[PDB]
Length: 77
Ligand SMILES: [Cl-]
Ligand SMILES: [Zn+2]
Ligand SMILES: [Zn+2]
Ligand SMILES: [Zn+2]
Ligand SMILES: [Zn+2]
Ligand SMILES: [Zn+2]
Ligand SMILES: [Zn+2]
Ligand SMILES: [Zn+2]
Image (spheres, rainbow, N blue to C red):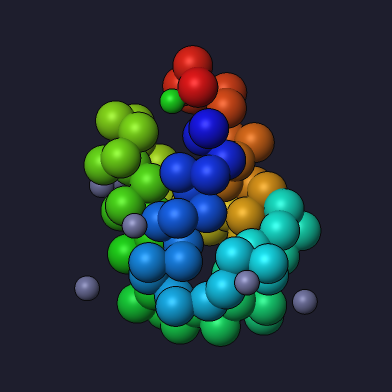
């Protein structure tokens, strides 16, 4: 599913265990993402799902849930 694909991208990048990759988990505060990690995650989500995440929207992506909910409104699943 889209959800699992997103979680896998996050696990690959951060080396965090999937049990912690929940919808309300903050990339920075909960998953330990540093500034480079967040830039790389956004880049990865864009390339994987063939969409763009403009800077203004990227700044508003703080949790795993934000990414999933946003993507579900941009792709079919
Ligand atoms: Cl999809
Ligand atoms: Zn993988
Ligand atoms: Zn486990
Ligand atoms: Zn937290
Ligand atoms: Zn890199
Ligand atoms: Zn890009
Ligand atoms: Zn972009
Ligand atoms: Zn916007």
